[PDB]
Image: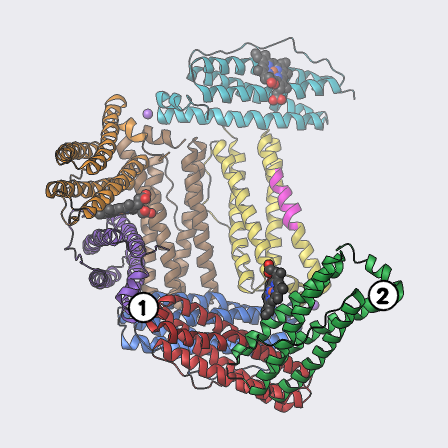
Chain colours: A purple, B orange, C cyan, D green, E brown, F yellow, G blue, H red
Amino acid sequence: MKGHPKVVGQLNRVLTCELTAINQYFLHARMFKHWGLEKLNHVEYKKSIEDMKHADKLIERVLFLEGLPNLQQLEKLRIGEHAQEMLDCDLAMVQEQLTLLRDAITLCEAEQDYVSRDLLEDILEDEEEHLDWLESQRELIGLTGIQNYLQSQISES
Amino acid sequence: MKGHPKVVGQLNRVLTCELTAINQYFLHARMFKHWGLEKLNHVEYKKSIEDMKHADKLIERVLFLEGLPNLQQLEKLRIGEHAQEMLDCDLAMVQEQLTLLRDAITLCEAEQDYVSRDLLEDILEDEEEHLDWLESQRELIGLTGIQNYLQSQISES
Amino acid sequence: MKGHPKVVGQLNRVLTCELTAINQYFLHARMFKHWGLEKLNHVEYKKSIEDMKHADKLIERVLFLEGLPNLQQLEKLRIGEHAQEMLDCDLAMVQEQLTLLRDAITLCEAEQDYVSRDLLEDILEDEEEHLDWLESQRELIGLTGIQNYLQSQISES
Amino acid sequence: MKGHPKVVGQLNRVLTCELTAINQYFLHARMFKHWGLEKLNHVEYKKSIEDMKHADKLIERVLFLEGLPNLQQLEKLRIGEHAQEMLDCDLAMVQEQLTLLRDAITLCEAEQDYVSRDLLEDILEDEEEHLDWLESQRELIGLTGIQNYLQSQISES
Amino acid sequence: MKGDKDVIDALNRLLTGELSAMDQYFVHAHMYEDWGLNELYERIAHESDDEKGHAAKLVQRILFLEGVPNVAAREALNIGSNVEEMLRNDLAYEYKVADDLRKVIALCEQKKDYQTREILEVLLDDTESDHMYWLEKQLGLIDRIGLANYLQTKM
Amino acid sequence: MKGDKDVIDALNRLLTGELSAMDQYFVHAHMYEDWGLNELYERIAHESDDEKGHAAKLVQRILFLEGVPNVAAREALNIGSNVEEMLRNDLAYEYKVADDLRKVIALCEQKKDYQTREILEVLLDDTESDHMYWLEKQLGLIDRIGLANYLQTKM
Amino acid sequence: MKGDKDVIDALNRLLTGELSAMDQYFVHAHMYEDWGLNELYERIAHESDDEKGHAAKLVQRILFLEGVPNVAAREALNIGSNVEEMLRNDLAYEYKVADDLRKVIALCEQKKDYQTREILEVLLDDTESDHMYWLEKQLGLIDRIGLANYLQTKM
Amino acid sequence: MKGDKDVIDALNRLLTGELSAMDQYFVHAHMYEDWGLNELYERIAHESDDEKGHAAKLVQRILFLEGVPNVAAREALNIGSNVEEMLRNDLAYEYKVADDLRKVIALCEQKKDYQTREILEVLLDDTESDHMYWLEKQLGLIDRIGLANYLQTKM
Ligand code: HEM
Ligand code: HEM
Ligand code: HEM
Ligand code: NA
Ligand code: NA
């Protein structure tokens, strides 16, 4: 089905941002593994796998809409040096990506692209569950301290 | 363990190339799925998963060697329009990446980095098994024709 | 039970034709096996087994009706040289045998031989399912070509 | 929850008596085992285990009521020389302890301590089932004689 | 509940569409079976069953909204004579159904009838992601391997 | 094979009948479900499925006989407004289908088309022994226990 | 995230509605059990549990949106005295909840808060397709079989 | 049976208490979940469920005693802002519930309503031995290990 050019452009931009998220989440997961923080590894890895599924769905939607998926471009990665900075960078990226998703859902509704909108709404609920998790982690660092919080991440389960 | 700067640079370059391979293989797998060629989808997807594992191992090795994994840079993607062109682009990328791996193994041996060399040798055997598969596919297209070859890819198993 | 002489004669003629069908179908199945066309082997063999069951039922009915089953006579066999000719010969024989079955069912109804008629109606439905299959095969040869059609018969399942 | 001082005192006195019961029942069970009366062993041991559970519940209740459990004091033990005397000593102790439990239940009701009263009522039903068993044993000794009664205790089951 | 009158009219037009789709997929599946193309027969028969499920959902929604479902009306069927023509007719008709579903989803959004909106969104998701996509893949495969190779895979 | 032209026409009229039966049983089952009468909903829905099976058999027979199945034409549906009316409409329509099936069985016997005869005999056996009999039983039960007791059993 | 202030107010009004629904369904289920009508007791108790699930989802959404859930406020309960009155009160209250849910879904669409929109769309789908429809079916059954037959099925 | 009027009034006050407890434990469990303190979330949610069970028992008893359960009234909720405050509010409210339960058990003993007495004795046993004791243990642990160690165990 020939999709709207604006919808394909928005999907390609959400795809760029999902790929940037995959890369940042995997680098952060492996930086966490390198420090022995295994539960943070596990969370960031499953989140990178999740954005992997999201990018897969966006590529398939852009292909179905007879567009050209743009896997070449990536955004700038925010790689932190320590756990708090990495969590803040992840938070900032989730927030930017949620703003982007909301703009794309608005445009998909304006163009009567309703299955693109359903796709983007699944991506939105997932990204906003991870936003919830990151805010929980920040509150936990504020509550128990960074040393106690990091001690809880040593064991993966 | 503090690794050699040259070995970390070579590992980071092999990492750039493994990430480029992941992206190209996934785009090609989903272009194949979009055309109903399901067995080609499956092969290219498992190959992208394999280069995914390779990039994971390279990131972990660069981190263990107290280097900074470079997940930001990617090489130029060769995306084909039809099956033969996509297979040729995959072939060209495997060949370039094998040359790179051989240079990195030589350097790792010259620096007595033997576990880096073992890592790169596993990546080499995998990449060169996929080189074998791509050459098999080209011979099969030459033997049965492109229409017969593509008909064999319709069903995933 | 003493059956009508006309009904026993018709049953004996349908029996001659069922035996001729058994022989032709088995020769054709083994000619197909000799050429490596295994799925055609399997079909023609199960069809010969089916006409075998039909001849068994006709013999038992002629014996119950105090007649003499005639297993000595056979009709002329149409043995083809290639797959299409063999399928056409099978088609011609099914059509002749269906005409015969319809005449016999008409006569069985005229003589109030209703269980003979039920027997012949089962034979009719079976022969006319095989007629359907042969017409399907001819349409498939017309659709995919003889080389593609024969390639689909190489593997038995 | 801060409990009434009178209720905590009564619970501590019931606890002293439950501990004395544990000690007397275990000494009697092992005196029975030493004589080969195994079923009497088993009964007196399960009764000592039961008073063990009772003392556990009383300690937990005195602790919940912000009191100090008194496990130091014990009452005088009535240790018999022969089976009948041991059963009579057990009977006397059960009767004294039942009088104590009834006084404590009355006081717990007067102080609106209703979960203390429920606890003490479970202890009362248990102690009074053992009173029933001891009276049954005395009637059985009167009915079958002491030699026949003791012969029935040789085998534990 | 009492549904909007325009929403019930649009649901009834969608019902006519789904019922015509059912008939066309039914006769096409059986024309595929008559030709020995059992894989197309099975695929198109399952799609006729999915059209029956969509029509059931639409009838249930029209009755819940206190409307009268119109199962008597039928659109003109476009029956093909050869495999490519039947696939192209199924694709044309899926395109028309998707367009009409989008119009009715817009109408349900304007009329605040959100639940009809999600029923029709599930219908549109099936129409696009289940059989329009499959038909486009099939026509692309016919273009790539040829019609005789394509039909050979469908036996 | 090449079927008799009259036999294919009669098979196509039977097909129109079966398809109209399917539509009527479909809307009636869903009208029963809308009213909480789930036992009637399930029974009438399974009868619509049996009509779909009969229509599949008729379409397969018409295609085998080298005819063109007519799935576009539909007879007028007689939709009831209350339970007794819908049961009586289903009964009237089963009666019409059975009469038309008998006429076509006679025709298939005259035209020596015995296999179409047994296909239609299986269809007539279902029409009589599966749902005409059931509908007569249901109307007799309504007469015996009353409509309010009868509908109470159907929930 | 920081939710829109109007979206949190509307979510809190929906929460008050769901909590009042829970209380009303709770007391109605137990009034049904007191009368031996165990099928209505079980149905209405499960609906009170579904209202508790909806209220949990709304509270989670209000807390995620950095609002303060209001579980203290309660709307006036409309408790019936006989079965028909309690069913009609439950229906009136489901109608009010569905209307208020539609208003809040419109508001979430205007305020770009799409995720609250789908949470409320799931809530509206339950309200319509789970218990408003069931209540309308029950009242129609009371109309068809009578109240004494209807109550006999509910024991 | 016809229960004593004072016993039904006291049971209704206990019901108001249990329902307010349910609301407070509900919002506190979800405030714990919003903060990543999943162990407190799960514990306090299960306590809200136990309050729902107690309220069900009280409503059943009030209806059996031919009274009218009051599920509309609610006491003022005391919602904390930080973990210690919410635990202390839950403890204060458990203390109030236990005091009120003791008063009603005394009343049921004076009014010879023994069965209400054992229902309330089971409720008091849960209130004391299930969650008042747990809350006192939690506050003592906060005093022993500190609040940051205590909250670390609750994730
Ligand atoms: C730094 C780059 C990446 C790394 C290191 C990486 C690593 C991985 C790993 C280790 C797995 C699990 C493999 C297995 O256990 O079988 C995985 C899964 C997957 N990846 Fe990636 N990946 C990367 C980028 C991407 C990209 C860019 C895409 C798509 C555009 C992608 C798509 C997928 C998919 C679809 C899966 C399957 C999900 C699953 O595991 O269930 N990946 N990745
Ligand atoms: C009067 C003629 C014949 C009759 C009535 C007859 C009947 C039968 C029957 C009833 C079976 C068993 C079918 C089953 O239960 O699955 C059978 C098996 C078989 N027939 Fe015949 N048959 C006849 C002639 C022939 C001829 C001429 C051939 C080969 C040239 C043949 C080849 C076979 C074979 C290979 C089997 C399988 C052996 C087995 O049952 O394990 N038959 N036949
Ligand atoms: C303050 C005094 C005591 C208390 C509160 C107490 C409590 C308990 C409890 C609760 C059990 C486990 C029962 C069960 O779960 O089945 C137990 C087991 C036992 N007790 Fe005691 N007990 C006390 C003193 C004694 C004494 C003085 C003896 C022996 C001279 C004794 C001998 C045993 C034995 C042999 C066991 C079985 C071991 C096992 O549980 O596997 N107890 N006790
Ligand atoms: Na071929
Ligand atoms: Na009745």
Q: Position of residue H68 (x, y in %)?
A: 59, 85
Does C2 sit above or below residue C77?
A: below
Q: Is residue G35 visible?
A: no
Q: Is residue C27 visible?
A: yes
Q: Which residue is mark 2?
A: D141
- Counting from the top left corner in percent of width and height, residue B5 is at 11, 44
Mark 1 vs mark 2, CA separation in Å: 93 Å
Residue E63 is situated, as x and y percent measured from the top left of the image, at 48, 63
Looking at mark 2, is its residue's CB closer than 8 Å to ligand 3? Answer: no
**Between C70 and G2, which is closer to the camera in this rendering?**
G2
**Chain part drawn in magenta:** F121-132
Q: Is residue B117 left or right of residue H17?
A: left
In the rendered image, which residue does mark 1 sit on? E110
The answer to which quarter of the image holds residue A82 is bottom left
Q: For the point 53% across and 21% down, which residue is it?
A: C95
Disc 2 secondary structure class: helix
Q: Chain of mark 1?
A: E
Dividing the picture into quadrants, the one containing residue A21 is bottom left
